[PDB]
Image: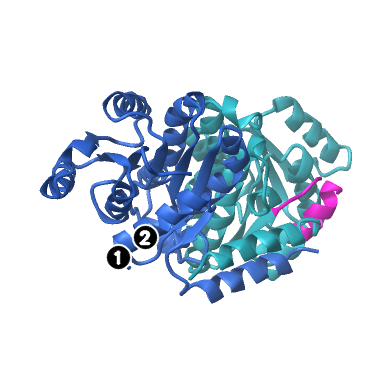
Chain colours: A blue, B cyan
């Protein structure tokens, strides 16, 4: 899809990959709504754009992506203030990792709430409008290569959630396509510069690419896992 | 591990795959605790074994695997009544499929609660004892080939949950290994006789196999997905 003239709503938008994506979407003609849990991060992020004389095209919303009522409110605020959005970037995450025997129900609940239910809540809250407005759109979900390559037990919660996000994104593709909404799952490793990731995401939105991986260092470990899965099949 | 003289706790144990696993574990010398949400199913399953003079080796518990308090109760009752368990089969599932546009938060919460949090709750409630008793054990989680091969959007919730269970099982392996507890993820297709699946699980427990797939029909479709993932990697 064409990025020019669109509005992008970006969770975890005040730092890291989310902020790199923000920069490159704005550079390609999008207006921005940055959502994040930290007030100070959001103000710093908009100040960056302020210094580049683009403050009027960036709005910020303090948001907990696990709060479904807040997510619905944010979708209405986005539409009112900046329009749309046409582009939804579900990028917020957290890392609940630690010795697996020390893991608690609270770790599981929080880990899944942000990393898995965040994107689900975004899809639930934003797609009714994205479908109804009828001008297409795009959804990017940030997963991780930790959702694909074999991971150790101290990363069980994170890996489990991010694997789910990969399959979620794959599986909703046909449903979203009915209303000309493309989907992409972003699978980072160690974050390469955020604006480089941003440009990969620009390409994925423009050309409707399902998969974006930032690194290839786990090609062989992934291949080995994939082969073991295949070998299990009679 | 040797199955003879062990106790197996099996969720969704009163029908389908769970009951086939129950049958073959008992045939290999395990005592059984069958857990299921349906009391009438449990009664029928109990009767089946009673008529084959195996009644005193089977115990039934009505259980909602998404209820953590009930799961804690079940672990206490299992240990008291039948001992152990040495073998934990997290097999309960449900399918909230339907047009993805019409999916509700309730569909997602139910789908994830049973299919993903069920096994997590089983692990959390049962593995402390399995570790403490110090005689090792085995955990089988029932996922699905739907968690691996590309699925249509109307199956998004099920596919998402089952993909997560595959990764859950992979990642916890090294933690469970510390206490000589092996793990297996079972990935079924269309259910082939349940007892045939049961024998695959006997083999997995005896030989500590990480993966069991019941069908080879999705080899090529999985290969294509895996290749697309690999191709995304720089």
Q: Could you tell whether A109 is left or right of B142 in the image?
A: left
Q: Secondary structure at mark 1?
A: loop
Quick one: label 1, few (<14), some, or many (20+) residues within 10 Å? few
Which residue is labeled 2 in the image?
A197
Label number found at residue A107: none
Where is residue A36 drawn, in percent x and y?
26, 41
Chain that bears disc 2: A
**Residue at coordinates 70% horizontally, 39% vertically from top-left?**
B59
Which residue is labeled 1 in the image?
A193
Q: Secondary structure at mark 2?
A: helix
Where is residue A123 drawn, in percent x and y?
46, 35
Chain that bears disc 1: A
Between B56 and B147, the one nearer to me in the picture: B147
Q: Quadrant of residue B199?
A: bottom right
Q: Which residue of the protein is positioned furthest toward the right in this rendering?
A: B52
Same chain letter for marks 2 and 1: yes
Q: Could you tell whether A104 is left or right of B103 in the image?
A: left
Is residue B194 on the magenta stretch? yes
Is residue B74 on the magenta stretch? no
Q: Are marks 2 and 1 in contact (CB under 8 Å)?
A: yes
């Amino acid at each position: 899809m064409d990025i020019a003239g669109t509005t992008a709503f970006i969770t975890g938008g005040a730092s890291g990959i989310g902020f790199g994506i923000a920069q490159r979407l704005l550079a390609n003609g999008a207006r921005l709504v940055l959502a994040d849990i930290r007030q100070d991060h959001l103000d710093e992020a908009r100040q960056f754009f302020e210094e580049r004389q683009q403050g009027r095209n960036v709005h910020t919303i303090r948001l907990d992506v696990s709060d479904r009522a807040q997510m619905a409110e944010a979708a209405r605020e986005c539409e009112a203030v900046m329009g749309g959005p046409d582009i939804l970037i579900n990028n917020a995450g957290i890392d609940p990792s630690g010795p697996f025997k020390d893991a608690t129900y609270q770790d599981w609940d929080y880990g899944l709430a942000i990393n898995l239910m965040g994107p689900i809540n975004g899809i639930m809250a934003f797609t009714p409008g994205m479908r109804a407005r009828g001008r297409g759109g795009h959804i990017v979900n940030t997963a991780s290569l930790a959702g694909l390559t074999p991971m150790p037990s101290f990363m069980a919660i994170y890996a489990t959630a991010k694997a789910a996000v990969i399959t979620l994104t794959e599986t909703i593709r046909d449903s979203m396509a009915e209303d000309n909404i493309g989907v992409t799952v972003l699978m980072p490793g160690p974050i390469m510069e955020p604006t480089e990731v941003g440009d990969m995401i620009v390409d994925a939105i423009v050309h409707n690419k399902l998969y974006v991986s930032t690194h290839g260092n786990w090609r062989e470990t992934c291949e080995a896992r994939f082969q073991a899965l295949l070998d299990s099949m009679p």
